[PDB]
Image (cartoon, rainbow over all chains, first blue to last red; front, side, top):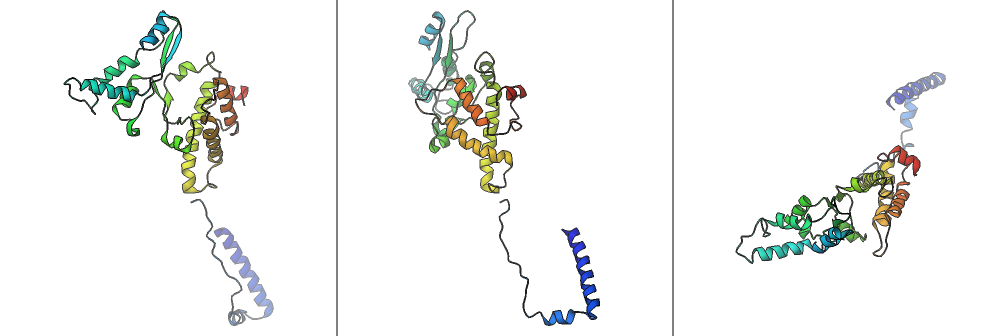
Length: 51
Length: 226
């Protein structure tokens, strides 16, 4: 999964850079302004593995 | 034992002498040994109880000139279930085996409550064979004992590492132990099983495992049976 993350971060950063180049400016300000609510959340599950 | 000696050597026939409550016999020896002025021995029982029990046990066994044979099965009461008690210790020294009746099995309701993990017979290999009982007996009993031990270990292991995390062998062995203590050791008080029928039930139990999992069974026995 570390190797997979190393690949996915590179490809996602490339996609974001391409989107920024197409838009003509960084979307950082808009992303920060749109941080009022969270669209992605992690719910903890106490999965029983072995003992 | 004198009746046994008569009927089994002077007459030519076999005898199965069954002696009940050797703990009661030892208590009787204690009563007489202290009926004299003799000082009590290791645990109250006389110091010569080894000889006094050897002279009772050893009057058995096949003889060259006679076609008879005395086989003894001394029923024995273990006080406080302590093997290191003098009577069980000396009987283990003089005799040639040990059949254990288990308090845990009896409480579970398994009649008869023999637990086969501690119990053994030294002279089994001289009885189980090709000419005596089925030719599979030697391998079947060894495999059954090994799988019962594995099942006991897996039953201990389930409560600590979860039922689903056990290996395939242990998962099958749990069902084998259940269908073993509930069907093989479990036996009616009036249910007589010939050794061949008992071996057939043993094989029906051993068919739970795949043919490759019966490690102790000889390949020829696996080919013929199973």
